[PDB]
Image (cartoon, helix red, strand yellow):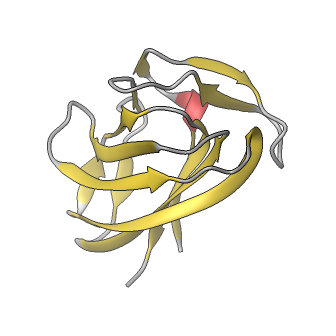
Amino acid sequence: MVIATIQAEDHSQQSGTQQETTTDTGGGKNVGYIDAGDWLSYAGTPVNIPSSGSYLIEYRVASQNGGGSLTFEEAGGAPVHGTIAIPATGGWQTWTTIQHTVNLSAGSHQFGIKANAGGWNLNWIRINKTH
C-alpha cells in the first residue's frame, strides 16, 4: 500500500543538482548531475507514517556507468533510515526501480536524500507499507 509518491524534482531545497526533462514513462522531469555530497530535501512536503515499522522505499533511477549510492534520511541528516546502491542501467534515460526496507517511526516525517557517490539520475521516490 502506497504511502506517498514524491517526484524527485519537487524538492523544497537541494544542493548540487539540476533538473531536466525525462523520457521515462509518464514524462515530466528528473534530477541529474548528482555527485558525492549533493542532496535533496523534501521537508516542505511532510509525509505521514501511520504506524511504526517496516516500509519499502522505491527509487526510480537511471545510471550510465553505475557506482552510485544514496542515503535516505530525515531532512537534516538525523535519523538516517537506510542506504542503497544504484546499479548501472546502461543509460542516463534508461530507467529502473530499485528498493530497500527501512524502519520508520509513526508520525510526520520530513525526508531527504544524500548522494554518497554520484553517477545516477532520480525520477521519483515511493514509500510503501509492508506490514
Horizontal relation, residue 29 to residue 47: left or right: right
Across the whole image, how many numbered discs are drawn on residues? 0
Residue at 61% across / 47% down in the picture? Answer: 61
Task: State the image quarter where residue 12 is shown.
Answer: top left
Residue that lies at the very extreme toward the left in this rendered image: 78
| 60 lies left or right of 84 | right
Q: Is residue 60 at least partly visible in the picture?
A: yes
- Image position, residue 101 (x, y; %): 36, 69
**Residue drawn at (37%, 27%) of the image:** 36
Would residue 5 be visible to someone looking at this image?
Answer: no
| Along the line of sight, the residue nearer the viewer: 86 or 97 | 86
Extreme residue in the bottom direction: 131
**Residue sitting nearer the eye, 83 or 91:** 91
Q: Nearer the viewer, residue 81 or 117?
A: 117
User: Which quadrant, please, contains the C terminus?
Assistant: bottom left
Q: Is residue 41 left or right of residue 8?
A: left
66 up-or-down from 127: above or below: above
Q: Percent from the top left, x then y, of residue 100?
A: 42, 66
Q: Quadrant of residue 28?
A: top right
Task: Please state the horizontal and vertical placement of residue 58, each as a whole percent of the image.
Answer: 52, 59
Q: Residue 108: x percent and y percent?
A: 28, 50
| Residue at 32% from the left image edge and 45% from the top image edge | 71
Residue 14 found in image quarter? top left
